[PDB]
Image (cartoon, rainbow, N blue to C red; front, side, top):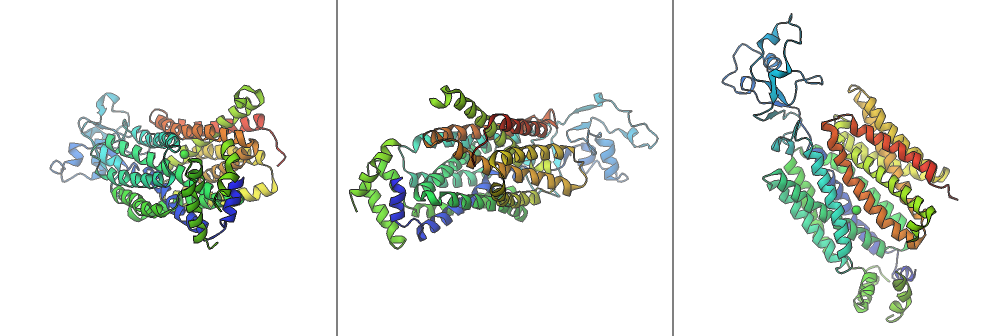
Length: 505
Ligand SMILES: [Cl-]
């Protein structure tokens, strides 16, 4: 750990580290708005088929109320309202006499919606759903779009992982900011949903590069004693951005203006990120010690206070920089950690992307999700001060699964209690995630802590990709996604009890 001593000698607690954290707070504040945008920009408004008798103003007989025309023009659907995707071929005038038994019409009188849809614009002025008619049959493309975005983060993280050995961390950060900004603003001009999804993929690829460069540069320029505090501050910045998205969507409500508000700040952040210095340690490993020493002298000058000694002192640590699968105890602990992290991230992203189903007011729910993650972190710290890691992890993940199942049990009325259970489940996943982040570091020794974290992270992003894809199944079985998230959360809590060891703590 000789580079940490060099950073201490360079002033590991100076003005530079604060300015660096603030500079990285800007993208961590803005990333949730881009990542979770589709909860608002792809909100499904109330909709029905266009029908000549109801929607062509020249055919509206002056003597009928719009409610009567709706009743005679659209059959009741499974839920308490007009059926969203089908109309009668001819107006069923027989359906207006109050003495007619409600079964006088057949399914044979219905057809799929052929002439498109008329959307209620009272709640949302425009969505991508209303732009490309993604309902009843095409409803799977929204969570598919979110899944494509998560796949963009996965592929980006992999490709940028490989490219990070050759290419530098400052220009990669700048390029990824520019790429995300350009692709994000370009999405408003997409003529087809396919072009939209492709631009979202390219945006997520850039976001993946943002995540990699920000975390790597931050850890590499923060001393080990401060890494945990800095990571906590970054988590709080992420949570502030998550809360701010609810207010931003409340402020504009137009998907195009919201997309601009999410994408243009990454244009502004790219130039500031261009001001940032490159990693001196990376420069050393690449065999560029003169530039690394120049960067150390620049940082030490900015924080307000010799050659050959630096590179010689860290030679062995750079030089030093399998048993996990052959050895049965490690095999089983590894497998357990992959299943738990996979099931956790599947349920976390299922919940965060399921916003329109969890509450009628998605803006309040998003704000509460940020507030309760903050509250969750404060109590995770309290729980860790009183209790142990395994019990809190298992209990929190079980409470999250129970909260999802309870949400499935809540009638549409009493919206506040449904919001309470959804917010509780989100908070529980926030605590479980922070516990898991600590517990991974405590369970694995450094050579395999590092080997394990790469595979765990890639399996977790696979989980993140699988979340919205399971959410796609709602069109056939509406109760299946939250049921799955509940049962998988409970089952992985059982995995924790049976398969993870008790530790010294
Ligand atoms: Cl990632």
